[PDB]
Amino acid sequence: LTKCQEEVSHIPAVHPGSFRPKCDENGNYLPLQCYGSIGYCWCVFPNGTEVPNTRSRGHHNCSES
Image 1 (tube, rainbow, N blue to C red):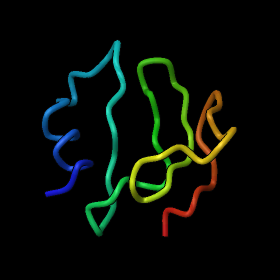
Image 2: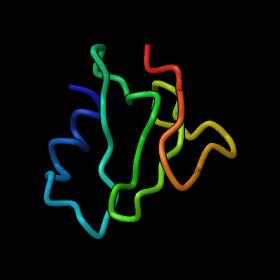
Image 3: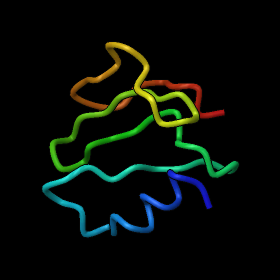
């Protein structure tokens, strides 16, 4: 596992009211993350750190390779 796959395991899909991460084909944080409970998203680096000022009202075309 990874910190992503751990947090995605430990925060179940029954997250409405909170954030839940997402992960890629290499177990790293998916380059787009979404706080579905408010419908917001941001881009992240593979380590899960937000890409500055991407935090917005919906999805964007991040490096999701």
